[PDB]
Each structure stands twice: as C-alpha cells, then as structure tokens.
Amino acid sequence: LPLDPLWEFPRDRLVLGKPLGEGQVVRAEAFGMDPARPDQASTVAVKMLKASDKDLADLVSEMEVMKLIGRHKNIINLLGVCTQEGPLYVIVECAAKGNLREFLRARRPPRSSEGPLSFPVLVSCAYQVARGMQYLESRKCIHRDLAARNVLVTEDNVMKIADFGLARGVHHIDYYKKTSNGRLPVKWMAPEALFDEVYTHQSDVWSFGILLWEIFTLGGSPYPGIPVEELFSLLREGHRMDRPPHCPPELYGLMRECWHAAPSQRPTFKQLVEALDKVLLAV
Image 1: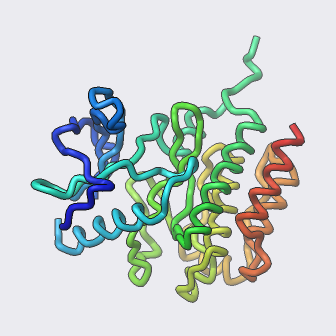
Image 2 (image 1 turned 120 degrees about the horizontal axis):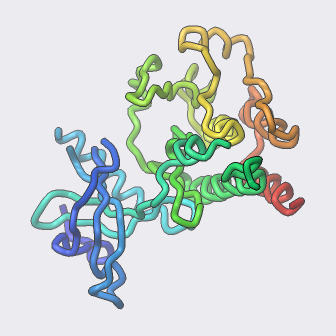
C-alpha cells in the first residue's frame, strides 16, 4: 500500500479499546488527530480486518471511497488511515449513542406522560438522514442498505449515515439471511433491486421510506410478522406497510411516496429534504 500523506496517521497515536461490531470496528483513543493539538485525546472508530485477500481489497476499496466522498455533517467521516508498517486501519468518526434503531428502541415511552422522544426530534432525525443522503447522492454514492441500524447517533443527537462506502456483494445476497440481531435486510430493498438487481439513488429513496417507518415506530421492525417467502409474494402484489400509530398523515404520505412502484415517481432526496424542512419549521 502506498503512502498518502494527506490521510496517514501514526498508529502509535492510537490506543485500541472496545470492539463495536464485526471486518471489525473497534473504539479507540487517538492523540493529536488535530495536529494543532498533538497531545489532545479524541474518541474514534477504527475499521480493520478480522482475513482473506478479498477481505483486504474490500477494506482498501471502502478506504478509497471515503477519501473521495469528502466531509459532511450527516455522514460518518474519514479521519485518517494507517497503511504503513502494520495492519490496515481506517479511522472514522465514533458516534457516542450508537445506531439509530437501538437509540429509538431504548427511548420508548410530573412528566410521566413524557418519554425522551418528541415529534420534532423524530422529524429532525429524518431530516438529517435525508440531508446526508442528498450529499452522498451528489457524490454519486448509492448506499444500497440504508436502514436505521446504518445511521449512527452522536452525543448531540446528530445523525450520521454509516457504511455508505461498502463493497456489497449485490450479486450474491442471501435474501433469507437473518442477522444475529434478527434483522432481515431484504426488507429494506427497493423492488427493482430485489427483483431486477438494479440500484439507483431512487432505490435508496425506497429504503429511506422504510427508515422513516422505523423512526415513527421508534425502531420497529418492518413488515411485522411477515417472513421472507411471504414478503416476495406480497411485494409482487404491491403490498405496502400500514400507517403506524401516532404518525401524522404528512409522514405516512412521505413513506408512501418513497414506495411508489416507479422509481421516477418517488421523491428525490432534495425533495425529501425540502418536505421535511417544512414540517420542522411548522414547529
């Protein structure tokens, strides 16, 4: 691997800590990530191999994607890399509150009538994800698995889209795959992706609609009670999820637009940002 001085960070300035998931991602302390404060500690996340040569190329691929995509408030940003004299590390921002799905589920409801989550904050979460996706789209990045579990939450409740630069094996998806936390990722796939193996930014818009439903069910799992075999047949029939409880029609409206059969008849991310902004400003 060649040295890129723009991004190289000394590995001896990292102290590896608790693993965050399984390549693998590990929480770490970094010293002098800002070269103006060389002895200052910060908390970062380090992506690394668990590994085959294919596994290595995929991580290098993600690294190069992240270099090109540039900075945005609502994505997990690249901070540095360690490529020389040791294992490949890709250092990115660490979001203190974990993923959005778990953030919502943990916060389900003199203030006994009040849970931690209010309507304007739920809308803000949706707006921020749309802003991040608008940015990624402007950089010609299709996410391909946009979902609440792939949005991370900072200490200040800022949404950051994660894992947007993954080499995903799109031509070998096990549609019946259930994760160790019980997720069926097929439930986020646009029909053109699932059925025809076509991905565009409009397929991410479909997934955003599913994410919207996750937000307004406070981390509910989509298509409740529906196994994959039934999901296939239901999608072929044009099945859409019901309006969740305590969800205004404006937001279910947006969900249904995101799930229009024709990709060109779904909103763009720019339109979603504008629509959600209007709801946010309506108080």
